[PDB]
Each structure stands twice: as structure tokens, then as C-alpha cells.
Amino acid sequence: FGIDMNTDYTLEEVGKQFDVTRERIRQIEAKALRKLRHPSRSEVLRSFLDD
DNA sequence: CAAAGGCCGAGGAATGCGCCCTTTTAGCCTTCTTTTGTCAATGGATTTGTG
Image (cartoon, rainbow, N blue to C red; front, top):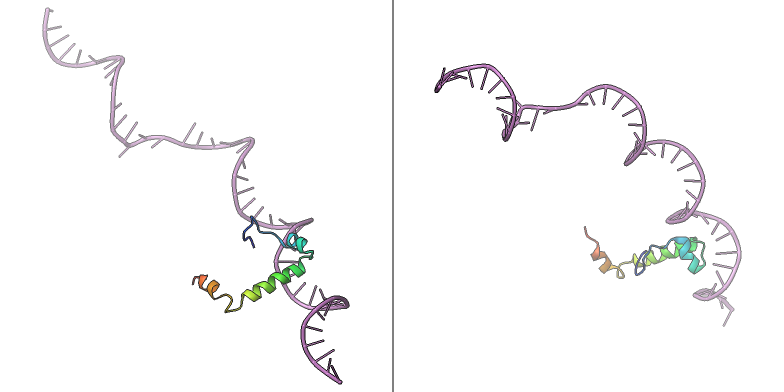
């Protein structure tokens, strides 16, 4: 994502700095998103949702 | 000898105002190549199982 930097880096350019061919980098993004998906870790972020 | 009237011009609303044809320009619309995000394999290095 683009937090605290002017991008928006993409998977190949990300995995360059981690030496992954973008597949493990996809997996790592997915794992972090799943971890933050948990309640008791994202109740505030839930409140930020508007609906 | 003047007066009526015919003439022209100087000033305004407005019921007033192009069309047909050639030629470029914009943009949308499809078709294809490439960067990118994804699913599944397939080992391989810690984590645990064991006594």
C-alpha cells in the first residue's frame, strides 16, 4: 500500500527488496492482512468502517 | 408670393438568424501485447515427538 511513501510499490519491485519473485511477497501480504483481519486486533479499524 | 406634399436620410426595435459541401479533429471502440496479481506444486529449514 502507499503508507508513508509516495507509492504504491508493485509486487516485483517489493520482492526485489525481499528477493522474492512476487509470489512469496503476495503470500506475506496475505498473511499480514489475515493477521490484522482478527478481532481484538482490529476493533478500532472496524470502527473506522462506515456503514 | 407660401404650403402641402414628395423625397431622402439619420436612428431604432426586433416576428430578426444560411446553406450546401469539403476536410480535419476527437474520441470511442475493438484487438492485441505486457505487467501484474493468483492458484497449485514441491521441496526445504525450524518445531515437536519421541525415549
